RNA sequence: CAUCCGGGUGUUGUCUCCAUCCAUAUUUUUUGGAACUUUUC
């Protein structure tokens, strides 16, 4: 399916996302999955409060993701 | 099936989510889980707006779908 | 290394006392010894106790509600 | 060979083309004490390496060097032996299952081999006329069935009379 | 800048993905990659690249109507007329390409077309110096041979990941017409053969380290590539992955269930043949043999493919190629397999570390560039460099260093050149670049002047950072030149042009050595006939426009001996006595093999900077070397080895220590030259037996006295130790049909050396592998003698590995033997004849 | 299905997990699952009162997994 | 430098023959951790 391949193609670029938690994470993406797992670096979190933090490495569960936000050149990619 | 869903492709859509937020933009790619990809997106939390760009939603998060405008040339 | 279901298999043989946490409820926990289990992570606890430290006194749990399984 | 006035033993030979072979100047670079002597330096070497042995080349073309060396097997006595037959020449040398119905896709048909096919494979390795099934018509005088025969070594058996003829035919072709 | 780009953009033939995404991708260090392509003659290399090129580009401008259809393989990267006309790749040309993979995540790939002719191994070495990993392409018919072993040995030695491609599979089926049962077996044998030379790792059509292809025809396979594409649709995904593990070796499925048992019941085959080879054969048989109407049904039935009548209206070969390219889609099986086969962390420290000392310090924020090959493009000479670190941009002022200088390792040290432009190679065009980033390989304008051959490029803003920085080691080319040509111009007045040209040739051809004699003659060394021929062509045509005289092909000789000294200073205060000794062939071989002493491998003497205890341990361990002698190893020469050996070493070691470098400098000086022909010395060990030193050394023991004195003593020692001449020898790799064997035997006899080390039936083909050895001085024309005497059948390659100089027959110093001029020397003496002709040239 | 996740690089290293109910745990990563069930040793709660325990965390619960030291 | 024997293409008029994408209720999406209350602006 194409909605997963687009993700794999944004590996390397910087990504923004939203979780069921309520917070948004922003960073370079290293690995993804068909599940929608993620592996990122130099993340800059921002919760409901506005509280910023730093997280060196992160793994996720896709189930917990609401939606992603992806770079603009990834609209000319082949489907 | 999914015959109807291909018909929606490349139309500006109004998508309500479980959070209440509503995303808007064209539809580029579609899934069996209802993962939608949307181009030039704008949330309307409510007298509010934000510019995102390319957004990939999950199936869990989506509630309803509705066409805003016809397919663009 | 140690896979997850092989780790739980040790808790059956040793008959070790294990406290179980719940999914969306931090206020509640459980206790007891492990007789048996299955592929879907359902558990048959023996001499199980509901834990303010209000210790209230053989049951079965659904695998959907667990979070932590901890030795002693 | 023409340009350099060095014909191959089989080959035709022309006049020089470049006139002057006059300068034969003894010199330190050249001198026989200084040189080391082994090997003929046969004319074939000169043609093969026109910019190595053959000092001062002019109007010389760069020669093709080496084709991959083709081991094709063609059978010319019994057609009965199949298309895919190991020849004398070649050197000696409890878990998961899926429905039976699924199988290799192409192999509904029992045998790859066709009576027609064996010839077809042979054709693949054939000359200009045959290996194309689409051709434009040409005149009778145009065709040169004769041509190939001179364009090949005479061979040892033939008497001088035909070997000369072979060279003469080549000369015309070359010019 | 923009104007330049706009003109430039028109020139290049555009592409489907576009530059912007390909340019966009670059920033991630992990994204993108570097890959080199090597393999023996005509293995397909260039055409493999051509496949990728034709996938990528819509136009293509160059293609004829003829070539696009079928018969003539289109050649890309053969942009040199010489190569085209010669017909074999000579100088490597990169292609850079944004490529997709099975996952659908594209990466930028730098591809390098290296030449597979044995004389241009230097080119392969240059490519390897930059590439992360290597694709090694083997002809299914040819199998593997000595050069393949050499290639894999070096590749792994330098921690270059290796992925195999078995090419020309169609030939196995169409040329040899092998049965499927036997075809599999043959492939398996080949697979086995590669594995035995490899150590610590084991491939298999199931690890996806081996790819099956026909470049000519137009297809590439991995067992993964196939399963997903056609089988995968048929069956549940969970199960399928396993299918591949149950596909290779010893597995047969009877009817839904497959049992490792041989084939019980009736008709039987192992799976590879069942689901792969058989249908492949059917494709071949079916397309040529079958009525064109019949075929359509199968395409829709088996493949869901629909051809127009114009696709039928071709001919067997062009039709077949169309069909194979139709069915088997873009070569992403290849790309995907490459992608998931290399781990940066495992190799990378190791590969960087070997070129440079392990370190490492001041990582990041710093520019670093390795310059390997230089490129004679349409305009000027470009410099090819690997983005080791940081970022380059136009007009950037960059410091440049050359390795021999580096060998050596503040004000005066740093020359610099601004970087005028950076372009990205694409075979026949260059794509304009504003900036270059770490990972990628690029074309630089204007960095050329600083360096001949290799150089290391760095920018350092830090004094400690500068101190840390380690210069790249000189590239170690696979072979030594040996072949010797003497040049003079036809007209002496044109010398200046020749001189310029020779320097240019050194820049462009990394294996060439140009030396200048007293006489003004130019000694050129090159690897072999063809190599030198190409040099001469370019020299006369491309660079100089001067017609020149060329001599009679010779060879460099080496000096040696087989078993006391007295000596006197020009101002008789010093007196030197040094023993000269034959060395153990084992020792010699150990020295010739450039190594770190890894695994169980005897330590290379260039590891001498490690504790002498360790060095001596190796000598004692591997040779039973005398414990004093091992402890007294001073250094190696420019070649062999120096030992201290006398009571005065105990009497006045401090005094002696003061004179080591003067000795040390001299010895390289003295051994680099020689007493017979001013040529370098091999297999000789020297031992200082006595050294008298001037009373009260009133600045008396000067370098002016002892350096030449030492030199003299060496020469005397060699002479009295009974000197000999050594001659370099090639390894002759000959491929022939069996009945042509006797011919080959006679040729060997006739040449001089007449030595064949081995004869091996090439299992699976009607061919022999013949290994011999041949004296380079008797090699002139050897290859053509073979080709002609076998009537075009079979072929030869000469490769210098092991670099062993055999004793030249005759006694080094006897007057009597030789016979008059113009006569090949009698066998008893080739040593005496060799010296005099060389002696005269020296003076 | 059942894509066995890329947790090989975290094995035998310290972690900072987060779970449902805003509760989090430190531990040495011993083993992992298809469904991302985890085995942690030397488990310490983060209430800020840190209690040593000695643990198998469920897959569903997991929100994320971090690394303390690079 | 020319001649000579041939070839292709377009166009214009003619002639003959013929027609006018898989099926999963038990942990990463479609058989729910949901439900409910209250305070602040
Ligand atoms: N029969 C057959 N020959 C092939 C195939 N692929 C490549 N070749 C051989 O490869 C030759 C042309 O390939 P090139 O790429 O030009 O040669 P190359 O491999 O670059 O050789 P170098 O330039 O010396 O490396 C032809 O003469 C073929 O014999 C194939 O699929 N079938």
Image (spheres, helix red, strand yellow):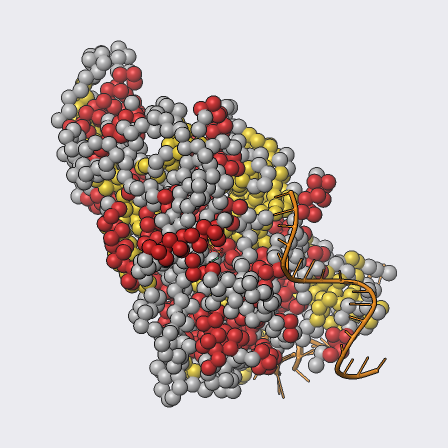
Query: Where's the N terminus of chain E, which quadrant?
Result: top right
Q: Is residue E565 left or right of residue E152?
A: left
Q: Residue at x 44, y 28 (%)?
A: E490
- The answer to whether A41 is drawn above or below residue D91 in the figure is above
Q: Quadrant of residue E572?
A: top left
Between A42 and E840, the one lying in front of the other is: E840
Quarter the C terminus of chain E occupies: top left
E24 or C59, which is in the foreground? Answer: E24
For residue E159, say whether it is visible. Answer: no
The answer to which quarter of the image holds residue G15 is bottom right
Residue E12 coordinates in the image, percent (x, y): 65, 49
Asked whether, in this view, residue B44 is left or right of residue A14, the answer is right
Tell me, yes or no, if residue E180 can be seen here.
yes
Left or right of D65? Residue E756 is: left
Image-based side of E460 in relation to B46, left or right: left
- Vertically, is E649 above or below E221? above
Q: Could you say which is closer to the camera, residue D40 or residue C30?
A: D40
Q: Residue at x 43, y 75 (%)?
A: E272
Q: Position of residue E458 (x, y in %)?
A: 53, 36
Q: Is residue E358 above or below residue E151?
A: above
| Spot occupied by residue C57 in the image (x, y as percentages of width and height) | 54, 81
Q: Residue at x 54, y 50 (%)?
A: E77
The single residue placed furthest to the left in the displayed view is: E564
| Closest to the observer, E110 or D24 | D24
């Amino acid at each position: 399916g194409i909605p997963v391949k687009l993700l794999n193609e944004a590996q390397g670029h910087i990504v923004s996302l939203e979780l069921t938690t309520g917070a948004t994470y922003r960073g370079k993406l290293v690995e993804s999955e068909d599940s929608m797992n993620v592996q990122l670096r130099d993340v800059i979190a921002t919760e409901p409060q506005g509280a910023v933090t730093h997280m060196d490495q992160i793994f996720v569960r896709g189930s917990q993701i609401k939606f992603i936000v992806v770079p603009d050149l990834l609209k000319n990619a082949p489907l | 099936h999914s015959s109807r869903l291909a018909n929606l492709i490349d139309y500006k859509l109004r998508v309500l989510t479980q959070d209440g937020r509503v995303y808007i933009g064209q539809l580029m790619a579609f899934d069996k889980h209802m993962n939608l990809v949307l181009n030039e997106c704008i949330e309307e939390r409510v007298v509010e707006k934000r510019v995102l760009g390319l957004t990939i939603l999950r199936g869990e998060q989506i509630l309803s779908t509705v066409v805003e405008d016809k397919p663009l040339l | 290394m140690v896979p997850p279901i092989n780790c739980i298999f040790n808790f059956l043989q040793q008959q070790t006392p294990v406290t179980i946490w719940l999914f969306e409820q931090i206020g509640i926990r459980i206790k007891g010894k492990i007789v048996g289990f299955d592929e879907f992570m359902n558990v048959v606890i023996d001499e199980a106790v509901e834990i303010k430290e209000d210790v209230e006194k053989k049951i079965l749990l659904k695998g959907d509600n667990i979070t932590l399984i901890t030795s002693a | 060979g023409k340009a350099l006035n060095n014909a191959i033993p089989g080959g035709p030979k022309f006049e020089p083309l470049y006139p002057r072979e006059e300068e034969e100047d003894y010199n330190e670079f050249n001198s026989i004490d200084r040189v080391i002597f082994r090997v003929p330096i046969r004319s074939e070497y000169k043609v093969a390496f026109p910019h190595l042995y053959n000092s001062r080349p002019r109007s010389v073309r760069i020669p093709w060097y080496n084709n991959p060396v083709s081991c094709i097997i063609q059978n010319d006595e019994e057609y009965d032996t199949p298309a895919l037959f190991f020849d004398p020449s070649l050197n000696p040398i409890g878990d998961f299952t899926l429905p039976e119905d699924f199988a290799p896709l192409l192999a509904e048909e029992e045998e790859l081999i066709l009576p027609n096919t064996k010839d077809a494979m042979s054709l693949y390795h054939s000359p200009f006329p045959f290996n194309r099934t689409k051709g434009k018509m040409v005149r009778a005088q145009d065709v040169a069935l004769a041509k190939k025969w001179f364009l090949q070594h005479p061979d040892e058996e033939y008497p001088v009379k035909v070997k000369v003829s072979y060279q003469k035919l080549l000369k015309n072709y070359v010019l | 800048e923009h104007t330049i780009f706009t003109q430039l953009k028109k020139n290049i033939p555009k592409t489907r993905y576009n530059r912007d995404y390909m340019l966009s991708m670059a920033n991630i260090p992990e994204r993108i990659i570097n890959v080199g392509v090597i393999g023996p003659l005509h293995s397909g290399k260039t055409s493999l690249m051509d496949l990728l090129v034709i996938d990528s580009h819509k136009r293509i401008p160059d293609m004829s109507k003829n070539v696009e259809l079928g018969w003539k393989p289109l050649r890309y990267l053969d942009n040199l007329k010489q190569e085209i006309d010669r017909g074999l790749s000579i100088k490597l040309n990169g292609s850079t390409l944004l490529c997709t993979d099975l996952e659908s995540k594209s990466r930028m790939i730098n591809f390098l077309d290296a030449p597979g002719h044995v004389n241009f191994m230097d080119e392969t070495a240059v490519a390897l110096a930059a590439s992360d990993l290597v694709l090694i392409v083997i002809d299914v018919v040819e199998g593997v041979t000595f050069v393949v072993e050499q290639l894999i040995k070096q590749s792994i030695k330098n921690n270059v990941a290796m992925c195999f491609v078995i090419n020309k599979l169609d030939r196995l089926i169409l040329d040899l017409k092998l049965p499927p049962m036997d075809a599999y077996l043959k492939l398996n044998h080949i697979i086995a053969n590669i594995n035995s030379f490899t150590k610590g790792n084991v491939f298999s059509p199931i690890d996806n380290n081996i790819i099956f292809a026909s470049t000519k025809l137009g297809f590439t396979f991995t067992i993964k590539e196939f399963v997903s594409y056609y089988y995968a649709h048929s069956i549940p995904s969970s199960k399928i992955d396993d299918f591949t593990t149950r596909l290779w070796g010893s597995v047969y499925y009877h009817k839904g269930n497959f049992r490792t048992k041989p084939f019980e019941n009736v008709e039987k085959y192992p799976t590879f043949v069942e689901f792969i080879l058989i249908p492949l054969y059917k494709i071949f048989s079916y397309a040529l043999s079958m009525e064109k109407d019949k075929l359509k049904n199968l395409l829709r039935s088996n493949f869901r493919v629909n051809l127009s009548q114009e696709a039928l209206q071709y001919d067997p070969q062009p039709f077949l190629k169309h069909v194979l390219q139709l069915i088997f889609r873009q070569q992403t099986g290849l790309v995907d397999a490459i992608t998931r086969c290399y781990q940066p962390f495992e190799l990378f420290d190791n590969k960087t570390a070997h070129l440079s000392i392990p370190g490492k310090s001041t990582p990041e924020g710093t520019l670093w560039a390795h310059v390997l090959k230089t490129v004679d493009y349409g305009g000027a000479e470009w410099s090819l460099v690997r983005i080791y670190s940081g970022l380059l941009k136009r007009g950037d002022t960059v410091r440049i260093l050359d390795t021999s200088q580096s060998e050596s390792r503040e004000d005066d040290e740093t020359p610099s050149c601004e970087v005028e432009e950076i372009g990205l190679l694409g075979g026949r065009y260059v794509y304009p670049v504003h900036e270059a980033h770490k990972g990628q390989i690029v074309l630089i304008k204007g960095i050329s002047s600083a360096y001949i051959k290799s150089a290391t490029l760095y920018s350092v803003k830090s004094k400690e950072d500068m101190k840390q920085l380690k210069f790249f080691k000189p590239l170690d080319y696979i072979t030594e030149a040996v072949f010797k040509i003497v040049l003079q111009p036809l007209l002496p007045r044109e010398l200046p042009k020749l001189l310029d040209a020779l320097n240019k040739i050194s820049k462009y051809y990394p294996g060439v050595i140009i030396k200048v004699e007293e006489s003004g003659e130019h000694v050129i060394l090159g690897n072999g006939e063809l190599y030198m021929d190409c040099l001469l062509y370019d020299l006369r045509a491309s660079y100089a426009k001067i017609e020149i005289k060329i001599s009679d092909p010779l060879t460099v000789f080496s000096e040696s001996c087989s078993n006391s000294r007295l000596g006197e200073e020009n101002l008789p205060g010093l007196s030197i006595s040094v023993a000269a000794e034959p060395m153990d062939s084992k020792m010699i071989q150990d020295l010739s093999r450039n190594t770190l002493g890894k695994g169980q491998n005897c330590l290379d003497i260039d590891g001498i900077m490690d504790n002498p205890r360790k060095l001596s341990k190796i000598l004692r361990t591997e040779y039973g070397w005398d414990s004093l002698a091992s402890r007294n190893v001073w250094s190696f020469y420019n070649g062999n080895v120096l030992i201290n050996d006398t009571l005065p070493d105990e009497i006045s070691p401090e005094l002696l220590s003061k004179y080591k470098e003067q000795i040390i400098q001299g010895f390289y000086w003295a051994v680099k030259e020689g007493p017979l022909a001013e040529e370098p010395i091999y297999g000789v060990q020297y031992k200082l037996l006595s050294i008298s030193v001037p009373s009260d050394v009133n600045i008396d023991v000067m370098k002016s006295q002892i350096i030449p004195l030492m030199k003299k003593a060496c020469y005397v020692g060699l002479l009295t130790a009974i000197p000999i001449l050594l001659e370099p020898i090639y390894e002759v790799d000959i491929t022939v049909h069996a009945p042509l064997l006797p011919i080959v035997e006679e040729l060997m006899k006739k040449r001089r050396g007449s030595r064949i080390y081995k004869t091996i039936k090439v299992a699976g083909t009607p061919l022999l592998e013949v290994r011999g050895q041949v004296p380079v001085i008797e090699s002139a024309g050897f290859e053509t003698d073979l080709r002609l005497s076998t009537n075009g059948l079979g072929m030869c390659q000469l490769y210098f590995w092991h670099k062993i100089w055999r004793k030249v027959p005759g006694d080094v110093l006897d007057k009597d033997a030789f016979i008059p001029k113009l006569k090949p020397a009698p066998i008893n003496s080739l040593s005496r004849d060799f010296v005099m002709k060389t002696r005269r040239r020296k003076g | 299905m059942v894509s066995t996740p890329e947790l090989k690089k975290y094995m035998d290293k310290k972690i900072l997990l987060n779970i449902n109910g805003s509760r989090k745990v430190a531990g040495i990563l011993r083993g992992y699952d298809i469904f991302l069930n985890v085995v942690l040793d030397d488990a310490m709660e983060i209430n800020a009162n840190n209690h040593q325990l000695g643990t198998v965390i469920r897959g569903n619960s997991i929100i994320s997994l971090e690394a303390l030291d690079a």
